[PDB]
Image (spheres, helix red, strand yellow):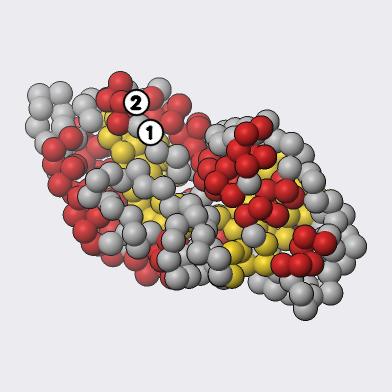
Amino acid sequence: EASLTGAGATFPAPVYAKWADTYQKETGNKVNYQGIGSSGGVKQIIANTVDFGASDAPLSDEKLAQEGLFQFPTVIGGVVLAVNIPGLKSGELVLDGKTLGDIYLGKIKKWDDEAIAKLNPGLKLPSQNIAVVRRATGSGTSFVFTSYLAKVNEEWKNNVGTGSTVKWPIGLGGKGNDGIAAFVQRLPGAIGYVEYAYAKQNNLAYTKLISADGKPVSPTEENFANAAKGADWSKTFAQDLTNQKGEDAWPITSTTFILIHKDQKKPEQGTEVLKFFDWAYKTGAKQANDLDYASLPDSVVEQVRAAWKTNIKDSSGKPLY
Ligand SMILES: [Cl-]
């Protein structure tokens, strides 16, 4: 029986927590996961204060080598826009990239604006003020969201850019994916970006979006998976899943990563960390789908196992997988 600690991204916390609970019920091993945001996860693993870190933003090959870290992907999720709009039911409103960016730039202030009406011919939109919400500190969800905005709105790209943190043009700060969810729920007229599970599990309304190919698409497990169908995983785990071509490709999709040290000074802990994740790939797919996270293809989990044998070892150089 092992006692393990992980910390980082809130984007996948719902599935890591469920995996952890089930794993304990079946093997007795205990995994404690702290959802503190991707930046804190990177800082904590580098500081050796946790057995494993978690970040939705991938570290470059050079940064990994500099810190003696190894990175591997777990699941595929999707970022959606949770909204609190009077009269409209969930999934009713459609936004495109350009207009979404204009809302986040503060150019569009009301829900019945001409640009939103044009995208929604049949809807009776309210004259409600839009209340924009965003993340309070360094966030992996913010990284994928701003990575998307920079591709579809040039003004955003040139003045604000992409990052785990950016100089937000407008918007109240919410802490964690759960904080943005709670803000949307209490604020009539609100719009906030969150990983899908955070909107669905809290019964929040969300919008549809226009794919890179120009078609309206709904956010679903299958549609997040579709956005990764063209990913050449064999080249690198650090795949960009925003604004991808293809039928029913959710435009704001992303995978997420686990970081661990290659030279394990507590080899028993590392050995157990790998067993937890392997068990998850082997048996946890139903738990991931129940939460609407798409599973990585078997080919990718095989890449991860092969890489574990080659990179994770004790101080004498013995492989831990
Ligand atoms: Cl936060």
Between 282 and 226, the one lying in front of the other is 226
> Counting other residues with Cα less than 10 Å from the Cα at mark 2, is it few (<14), some (14-19), or many (20 or more)?
few
Tag 2 residue:
63
> Counting other residues with Cα less than 10 Å from the Cα at mark 1, is it few (<14), some (14-19), or many (20 or more)?
some
* Residue 54 placement (x, y as % from top left): 42, 40
Residue plotted at (35% across, 43% down): 238
Residue 26 vs 314, above or below: the answer is below
- Quadrant containing the C terminus is top left
Quick check: can you spot residue 251? yes
Quick check: can you spot residue 146? no
Q: Disc 2 to disc 1, how far (Cα)?
A: 6 Å
Residue plotted at (64% across, 60% down): 96
Secondary structure under the numbered disc 2 in the rendered image: helix
Tag 1 residue:
59
Secondary structure under the numbered disc 1 in the rendered image: loop
Q: For the residue marked with disc 1, what is the amino acid?
A: Leu
Quarter residue 85 falls in: bottom right
Residue 104 vs 188, above or below: the answer is above
